[PDB]
Length: 142
Length: 142
Image (cartoon, rainbow over all chains, first blue to last red; front, side, top):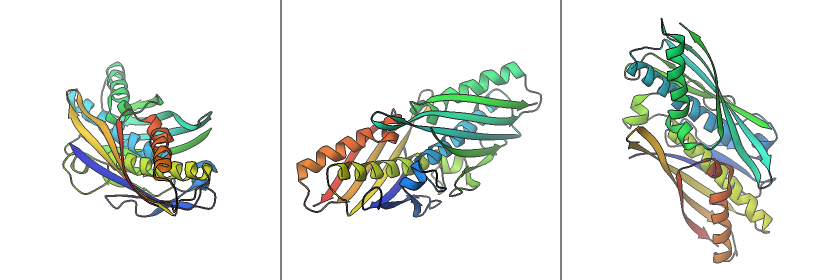
């Protein structure tokens, strides 16, 4: 199995405390995060946008793979993942991720493409591991 | 409802194609990713380490909060999230996330702490949204 690691550091309480997040690749190295950026809308990284990025990335790559297996080559795939963090009795929960994608695949049938993209939406590794509602809105250029 | 966004871009097929990943905060901005970095172990970002970073960050924040609710203030929390991407019949799947955390909470009861940290491991938002097995290994300095 493939193992990849992420890390975080936290110090003090939630209001007066702060933290940082990193990844083994180094793309993220002690990047600041906290209550402000996660719940108060202050610009900065947080768990949600990171999961959104991971999801957009896994979905896009999966769409390319499946398209290839169908004998198609995508010119470009641009996916956005909107992660919803809602308030619930237990606190908060990631309830939905809205995927928005613009794909360009030369001469591919609209009906055939839809079948492939819906399979990617529900079949990629990240979608499969998430419990949140996953929606998909796309635009095909062929 | 809080909304956070992530995105990704991909061009060409899976072997000769390539992609990038970004987040709205900018911590990730068109950072390269591909088959190489995700499946061949080449150093670079990928969906798995991003989920790991997100999980480590959520879990550490959640632990601080709960300790606070118990009347405790953590001196420091350092968590690493090890994400497993396994090959399965249908393709691949994120089967497990192993959390390892080092926490310093002066004077807290060992048993008291264990109950709290276990509740955080199972109850934080990111743990809650994941279907993968989540394990916890920690070392408390008290």
